[PDB]
Amino acid sequence: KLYQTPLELKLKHSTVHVDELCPLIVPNLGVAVIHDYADWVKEASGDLPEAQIVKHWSLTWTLCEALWGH
Amino acid sequence: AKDAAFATLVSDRFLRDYCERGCFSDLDLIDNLGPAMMLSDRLTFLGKYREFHRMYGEKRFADAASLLLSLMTSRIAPRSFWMTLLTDALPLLEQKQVIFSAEQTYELMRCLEDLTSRRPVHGESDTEQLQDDDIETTKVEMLRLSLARNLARAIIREG
Amino acid sequence: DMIHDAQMDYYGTRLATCSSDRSVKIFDVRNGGQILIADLRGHEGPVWQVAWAHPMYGNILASCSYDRKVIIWREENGTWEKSHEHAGHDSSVNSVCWAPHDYGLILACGSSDGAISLLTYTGEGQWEVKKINNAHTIGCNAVSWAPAVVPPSGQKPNYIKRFASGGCDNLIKLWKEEEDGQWKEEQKLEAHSDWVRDVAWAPSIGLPTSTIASCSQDGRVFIWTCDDASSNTWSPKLLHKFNDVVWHVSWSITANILAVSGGDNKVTLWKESVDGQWVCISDVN
Amino acid sequence: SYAGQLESEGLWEWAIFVLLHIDNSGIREKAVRELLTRHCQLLETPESWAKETFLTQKLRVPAKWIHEAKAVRAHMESDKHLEALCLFKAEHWNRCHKLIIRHLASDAIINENYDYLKGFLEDLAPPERSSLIQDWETSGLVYLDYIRVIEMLRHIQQVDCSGNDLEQLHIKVTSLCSRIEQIQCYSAKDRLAQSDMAKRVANLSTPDPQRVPLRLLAPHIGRLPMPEDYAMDELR
Amino acid sequence: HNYYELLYAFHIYRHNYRKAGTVMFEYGMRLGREVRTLRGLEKQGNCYLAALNCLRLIRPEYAWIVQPEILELEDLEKECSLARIRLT
């Protein structure tokens, strides 16, 4: 979450428009944030979330992608 | 009474009350202050100042006033009205021209140099010269300029 | 020796500190490095609180003292000279805060004689003294303004201009500016048992549920909140009860975490949970 | 909650992206304004890009608010002489000539560095023309005429005629300096800059006025109340 | 002859409109600032007295070049007070 590559990847997967001088998320199909959908599994390695608390996050992301995933 | 602390305070109050206008009157020829010898010889400065403010005899009165001011500015008669007396005496020297001071210009310069590096409080309505000023250093600058003019226009009188 | 109140500037710029030695030091914080710039001195009593102005009106910083006077020094070209000086109070000033940027450059100052001055800057350096007497019994002790809530034309929207003040009469009376020009007491909140120390209003982050925290000398911390807008219903809620008295009470802008400062010389961070009860996050120092 | 958690650590782009995905427009705009006012120099797109090549402009956000927030933060954290150039050149002033003129008055020293003052005076006209201003335009004109008068006095030392706009510039400088008498203003740096600009051109033309304010503030404040007519005070 | 030249310039200015004596005094003080403990203090006192006289004998608008008016006078007074406190 402290990298700019994730923000750049998440900003390109949404369609925003200027409405009354305010940006709103109209159409979105993915997000590269922490503990998201299928795009958050690649940002959880041994050099991003240490090693003592990465397996649980990966399992929670996989379960959410397999259950709440279309 | 107890010591000289009361006599010094009374002398300072008299000197502050006498210096308020152009002519130091108020308590003119009404000071006396005669007690024993040690407590009576300390009141000679006030008497000399009163005699110089009342009567005048060529440059003798000016020399006596300058000597009294130099003696009072040497940590003797306090230091409240000393700056005012010095500024009033420097206004009658040669602020607009050039004069002469035998055994007095160097003393006035030393007094102005010592009062500028220590503490200086001047508060006395003299005449038209004091009303046109603003800061306290203006009187010292005028006195220094007058002393320089006197030393430049009087030290070349060789025999 | 001992400092009283030290608030930051704008976006973490300088840090105006105030101690009991009548010295309003303005220290700069550059990358975590504390460095003093100037020492504004000109009060006969000890300095209490200090609040900085907005960046739209230059760089002003007002600080109250115990000499029955309020100094408002500016900052331009490295000259921290005093611009305005308000001394309309009879007793010592306890708290002195400013209003929002949308309403102008108003500054509310509470005294210890039961009055609340409101220095409203006009088109220049002239400030109108709009004080309101008979505001407290033993005197005011806290002053904080509410958030700027906006109410088919080309003009500025007139806000309600609300400001909740705390005093030593165990009543947090909130003020409201009428359409005539004078301020009046809207409602009172008598829920404390002793003298109210500090009472800062929580900033709304777009939600209409405006809250306001208060701290008294009895050790209780009340969090009065409103149910809806345009409804005089200030339901107080007890957050924590300590054995000692509390000093100041600040709130955050993101999660609105209440910073309870007081008790045994320690600061505690209180945050509202999902159940509605306030719990302590961690301990400072 | 996500925008607050992302902003409490130091991430501005993530916090802005989390706040932009809200429901209420009035709350989202306020959150975006608060996030821009809290931190704007760390994630700026224009003026030397260093935020991964346009980070806030790609989220369908206006660049006028971010630039204004960055200018307001620089005017409070950095100096006033360097923060005025980032506000007028950002194309988001909207009748902000008074703030620029007040900020540019801090660099009144260093007479040999008039290039920055000339550039500021030349750039202040573009913002006033873009913001549709055709009424209050005296401080910038006086500041532009002062530098030109100083340059003409430093280059030509034998000329002593009227410069047409010299009288208008002097009248504008006098009206700006008489703020304490017009609307009772307690300005210090601006008044000092105006006095310096009015006195730097008095050694060539005429300048009958431009002085101080009698003895009402010199013999009653601390023997110091801005010098002016020292020649008239020490001469006759 | 710097003092004589400054006096002549001040007289020529007063014989026209009188609006450059303070600027000349400020330029002279800036050119001859670093001196010693006694000479520098005397020069600072003379400059302060000249500035006070100029402020007392003037009444129109604002004119104070070579001085970064009110703020410059306050800074000069603070510097003089600091020098007097350090020398005593």
Image: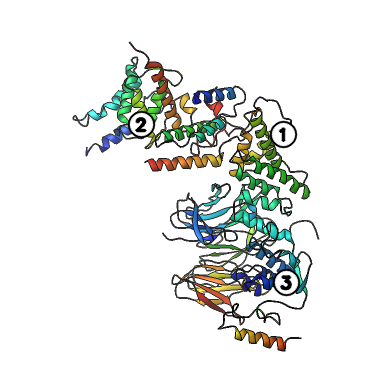
Q: CA distance from mark 3 to mark 1?
A: 55 Å
- Select label 1 or label 2 by which is in front: 1
Relative placement, left or right, of D113 versus D97 is left
D176, above or below C217, in the image: above
Q: Residue at x 69, y 39 (%)?
A: D144
**What residue is shown at x 71% (from left), y 60% (from top)?**
D65
Q: Could you say which is closer to the camera, residue B32 or residue B61?
A: B61
State the residue lying farthest toward the right: C152
Q: Which residue is mark 2?
A: B82
Which label lies toward us, 3 or 1?
Answer: 3
| Range drawn in magenta | D48-54
Q: Residues within 10 Å of mark 2 (few under 14, many from 20)?
A: many
Q: Secondary structure at mark 3?
A: helix
Question: Do pointers 1 and 2 mark residues of a single chain?
Answer: no
Report the residue marked by disc 1. Answer: D168
**Left/right of residue D172 with respect to residue C95 in the rendered view:** right
Residue B51 in picture, x, y percent from top left: 31, 21
Q: Residues within 10 Å of mark 3 (few under 14, many from 20)?
A: many
Circle 3: residue type: Leu
Q: Residue furthest front?
A: A46
In three-dimensional space, the C-alpha distance between marks 1 and 2, rounded to whole angstroms, equals: 52 Å
Residue under label 3: A11
